[PDB]
Image (cartoon, rainbow over all chains, first blue to last red; front, side, top):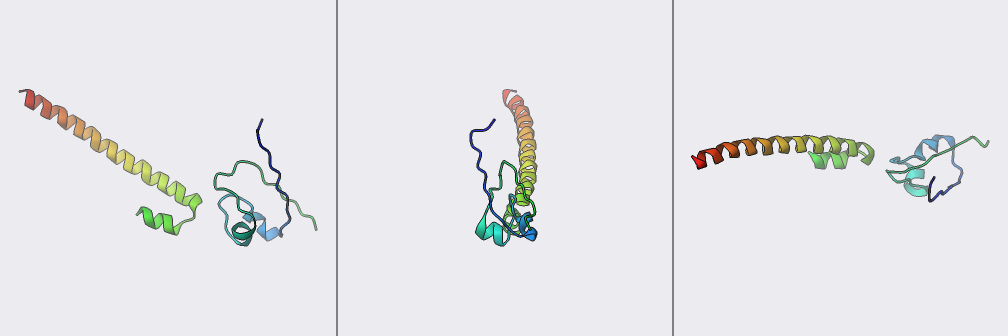
Length: 49
Length: 49
């Protein structure tokens, strides 16, 4: 059980999927969406071509 | 050098490196403190004599 669940939804390009993870850098990580280094939770990504 | 590790590596791996450094320095300090305790017991025996 958990006290807070926050589903954050968005769209990126495949090469940038790696950037959605704690401790990552790059365009998306630096300027669009930044996770904490101690992030606790799951990341899910699927092609939507 | 702690500063070089902080300035050079990203936080995810700099954290592990500083963990290593902290463990090492703590072990060195513990060894020094134990040696000081034993030598001080010797000196206390000498002072009692």
